[PDB]
Image (cartoon, coloured by chain):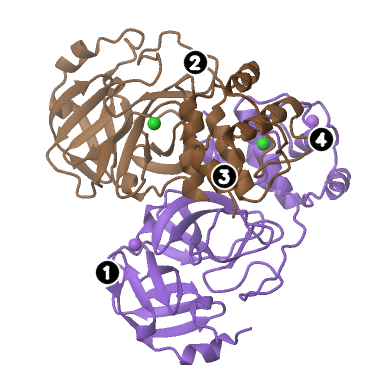
Chain colours: A brown, B purple
Amino acid sequence: SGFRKMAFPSGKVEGCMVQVTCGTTTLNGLWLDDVVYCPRHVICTSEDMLNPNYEDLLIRKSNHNFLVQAGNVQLRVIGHSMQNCVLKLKVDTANPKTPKYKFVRIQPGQTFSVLACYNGSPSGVYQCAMRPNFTIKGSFLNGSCGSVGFNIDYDCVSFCYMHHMELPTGVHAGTDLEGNFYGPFVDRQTAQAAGTDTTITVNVLAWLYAAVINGDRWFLNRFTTTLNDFNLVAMKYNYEPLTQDHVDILGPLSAQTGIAVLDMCASLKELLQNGMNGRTILGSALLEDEFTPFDVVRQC
Amino acid sequence: SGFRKMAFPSGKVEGCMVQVTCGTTTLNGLWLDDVVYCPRHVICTSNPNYEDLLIRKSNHNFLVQAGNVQLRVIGHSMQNCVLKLKVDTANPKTPKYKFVRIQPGQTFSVLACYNGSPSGVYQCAMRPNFTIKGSFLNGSCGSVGFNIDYDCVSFCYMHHMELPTGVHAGTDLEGNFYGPFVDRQTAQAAGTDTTITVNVLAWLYAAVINGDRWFLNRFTTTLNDFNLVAMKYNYEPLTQDHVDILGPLSAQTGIAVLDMCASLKELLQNGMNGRTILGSALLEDEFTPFDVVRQCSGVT
Ligand SMILES: [Cl-]
Ligand SMILES: [Cl-]
Ligand code: NA
Ligand code: NA
């Protein structure tokens, strides 16, 4: 029993973290085989942070301008290239600790673990979800850029996120490992703000199913709902729309617990109306939306 | 910025995890130097007296797998509730480490494992009732808890059982239980738990550092006055050493501990009036003062 935000074991990623330095700027890089991936804004200078022309800034660099340190070993950069907002540094040594890995671009609501690092050194690991507004609610300080987000289902590290910046509300924004930002953000210090965030309905329902599995039923009711009536209500609480894909996805948990998906939807509707009345669900007094249906099955 | 429940990077401990099988029982072991540590209840029962069951066992009754590799057991002894299996090979991945026993209220990371394979990492506090609110299914026994200071891993916890309330109990790595528990299938209950006052205060300081300030007021109180409130709300007593430990956070925010205690009083008496702190609608008590300092400053 029990239910917590569980990260994946971080060791396979720890052995890939390096420090990249350009001028006065140091951040983290990800060393897989003979390439180091990092945010391209490492080549920015204080002068042009509003409208950097990355192509012009990169053509001016030589390989020996990039200082890359893996622990106490300096790696030798033998080439470089930019892919979207990621810089790829070719190095003279393939990382002998490279795990089996792939690069995946995730959708909003998906979860992953972040290995927060500074100066190439891991600090901590935690779980995060990609919010509907394409931000993440992380824990980063300056120098954490290049820290990555990943899953390790089965045999194999799936890299899904690289950290690039912090938005004025205290939330965080970055790219996939092909260097495409999540959301409408750009790697410039021009004024930018996250869209209004919303709650990840399908994940809240998963977590209510987790609660039933863990043996708690107090929030159920004798009612059902149509999908459309559920969405009409839940939108008034800034919940994301629930789709037929989401209903399908919850099928397994529905079967495991014997509670129909749309009946659980009716329980959620009533929770939004009543609140908790001094009770908790899996130790929370809020409805939790950073566990996916897949996570619930993985942990329960 | 941001503030998350953060576990230590787990790779140093991942390379110490092995599978131990003996009889019908499979669970996890910790391989350090040439010894595998695991719960003594792995030994085959016939209400046990674990010494007599252990002479019946031959070294080759303990099957120890390190990944896809068998470790040869060449000896076995008991220390309190922990079995120590001498093996023929020192773990080449052994980190700098020591065995420590933690106090109630202190936090640590748990590397949850199944069949010797790390599955997940999360951060826990040793509760005042000497239990931990973990996430464990059958076969997690022998998973460990630890902190990291510099490069040194301090192992503090080994998992032995789940209690009827869904919380978990175990020992230090020297086999001494935390709490009034014994390792057998019997009528055992966690004592009434209480809230870790010094940690709630630390988390309110973390909130203030992250810009959450609505709960601050102009008022201050006395240790004796507050402890009467604490006692009423099933909060642990606050001691002068707790106040002194929070010194750094009081200096950094300009809110003296007894100033903050007056805030906690009002929160206890009046609730949070529909508001949240650091994304929580409850008062969170599994961050220590050191945890807040460490995360609001970036150690690796
Ligand atoms: Cl996805
Ligand atoms: Cl909460
Ligand atoms: Na292993
Ligand atoms: Na006050």
Compute the Cα span from label 2 to label 1: 50 Å
Q: Are marks 2 and 1 in contact (CB under 8 Å)?
A: no
In this rendering, the label closer to the viewer, 3 or 2: 2
The chain letter under disc 4 is B
Residues marked 2 and 1, same chain: no
In the rendered structure, which amino acid carries the disc numbered 1? Val
The circle on residue B262 is: 4
Residue A288, position in %: x, y? 60, 35
Alpha-carbon neighbours of circle 2 within 10 Å: few (<14), some, or many (≥20)? some
The circle on residue A57 is: none
Q: Earlier in the sequence, mark 1 or mark 4?
A: 1
Quadrant of the image occupied by residue A48: top left
- A248, above or below B38, in the image: above
Alpha-carbon neighbours of circle 1 within 10 Å: few (<14), some, or many (≥20)? few
Q: Which residue is mark 3?
A: B291
Which secondary structure lies at badge 4? helix
Quadrant of the image occupied by residue B37: bottom left
Compute the Cα span from label 1 to label 3: 37 Å
Compute the Cα span from label 3 to label 4: 23 Å
Q: Which residue is mark 1?
A: B69
In the rendered structure, which amino acid carries the disc numbered 2? Ala
- Please indicate, yes or no, whether residue B298 appears anywhere in the rendered image: no
The circle on residue A194 is: 2
